[PDB]
Amino acid sequence: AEAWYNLGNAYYKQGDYDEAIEYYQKALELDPRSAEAWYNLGNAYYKQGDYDEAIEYYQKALELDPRSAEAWYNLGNAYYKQGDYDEAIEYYQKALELDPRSAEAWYNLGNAYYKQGDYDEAIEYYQKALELDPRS
Ligand SMILES: [Tb+3]
Ligand SMILES: [Tb+3]
Ligand SMILES: [Tb+3]
């Protein structure tokens, strides 16, 4: 499994997401235990624009390891990209509960409320982002 995984990683690093997907899938067939590997497979689908696949593999990562702020955040991002703003909000909140340090994540939670048309919460979360990083 580890060898196929590392070949997927090398393709991923040069932006060959369809090859990364084929080799990650072969790795996971041999050993499905790593939350990180399912997360990397989700990322490959996300980079290709196949958000429904990214969601299925991020969910599998989080079933294995639910304290990954990064997996919750990317899950939120995949729902955001489908226009599922209510889900993005839920998973962004879960991410920020685990790790409130990223200005960018507070901003994206603000963006999801804005897209819902809930301007109060958009302002609340944009203000949290700008307190952390006022440069954009
Ligand atoms: Tb290719
Ligand atoms: Tb596609
Ligand atoms: Tb699909």
Image (spheres, rainbow, N blue to C red):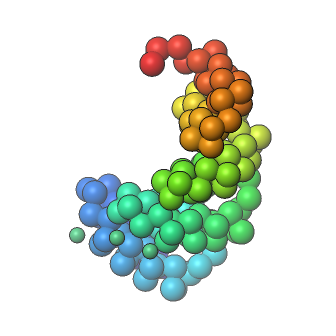
Give left or right: position of 116 versus 82. Answer: right
Q: Residue at x 26, y 56 (%)?
A: 14
Q: Residue furthest bottom?
A: 29
Residue 15 visible from this viewpoint: yes
Residue 132 visible from this viewpoint: no
Total numbered labels placed on residues in the image: 0
Residue 85: x %, y % from top left: 61, 50
**Regarding ligand 3, which quadrant of the image does it lie in?**
bottom left
Q: Relative to the observer, which residue lies in front, 53 or 116?
A: 116
Q: Residue at x 63, y 75 (%)?
A: 33
Q: Quadrant of residue 84?
A: bottom right
Q: Residue at x 62, y 43 (%)?
A: 116
Q: Quadrant of the C terminus?
A: top left
Q: Relative to the observer, which residue lies in front, 77 or 10?
A: 77
Give left or right: position of 65 versus 108. Answer: right
Q: Relative to the observer, which residue lies in front, 83 or 72?
A: 83
Residue 118: x %, y % from top left: 68, 35
Q: Is residue 121 above or below residue 88?
A: above
Q: Residue at x 55, y 62 (%)?
A: 39
Residue 124: x %, y % from top left: 71, 24
Q: Is residue 115 above or below residue 80?
A: above
Q: Is residue 132 above or below residue 39?
A: above
Q: Quadrant of residue 35?
A: bottom right
Residue 43: x %, y % from top left: 46, 59
Q: Relative to the observer, which residue lies in front, 67 or 109?
A: 109
